[PDB]
Image 1: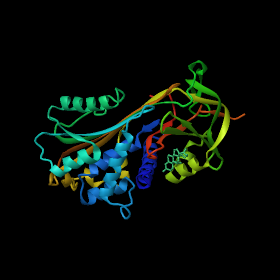
Image 2: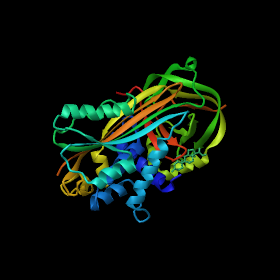
Image 3: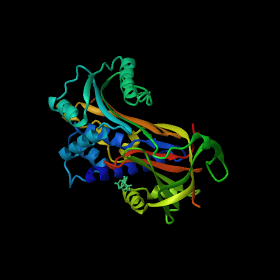
Image 4: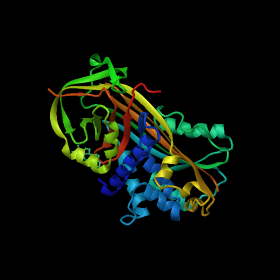
Length: 339
Length: 34
Ligand SMILES: C[C@]12CCC(=O)C=C1CC[C@@H]1[C@@H]2[C@@H](O)C[C@]2(C=O)[C@@H](C(=O)CO)CC[C@@H]12
């Protein structure tokens, strides 16, 4: 395990989560933290000076204990690990850059992009925005096996570069649900309001379990075949906001360390599909990533000159939970214009 | 004699054993939400 990378990426996940819920407190949340971390790490490869340090600190790296080169190597090793072949679980993460043909790129940037982030450089004619949009969306659709289809909604005709990350995940439960045991049941939006959903069930299950009485919530870990699992956190009625305010790397570690095996008589879990798309601009600024969007942007590591600036970071994610397993995908795009 | 019933908002955190990556993080406030 890369302890340093995992600590930054987990801090970043929960910091991003809190900002998303602050922005839209009544909405479903679904996103891929590791997709966004990797896309922004990829962006920082070309960043200099305050633009660079804001990105790395915004990603929750402690720059007094790590360096940019170590960070990029850590992401290189992460991508290699995630993309290793598996017979049990489908997992893929890719990066790409779409560049205007006439834009002069530093040889060291394109070489580092391929070497560290696995990224090719696709010559893209952004002035034909419809075709450029279709190319990027097709790349993402191919990478997510059809799941993420419209990551790019609008694309400025004067765009110079788009960095893209995608993640694709499909896994079977170690203990799958029997669809004969799925029945329409209430899902309570509030104490007085509910919707009817297909409620899946498992019976006589022994799984890791922890009742967090101080935080008024119950935590269980369900397993996928392969090296992935899922922490489910079930706050008691009306306590979701109280649990969310305690979300952190420390809490997750404590939950992990507190789990004990327990025989569960019945476990009820909805079958559901949810998706969200995000404009991350305001969230990234709240996290301190500011200069990359301004006239003072320093992306001179891409071109040799301070002639590029981020216009928009977007993210889209989908989560499907059903009797056989889970399918989830997400993609992140960093749109970049002239400066 | 223990029942765990996800019939109200809950969180889902999909994690990798190898890297400790959080692949996906989710709050399900409404499975049938627009
Ligand atoms: C929370 C945890 C540590 C803190 C951190 O930065 C990120 C994570 C997420 C993945 C977590 C780890 C850690 O608890 C060990 C695990 C869970 O408890 C493993 C076990 O189930 C124990 O054998 C499988 C999944 C692991």
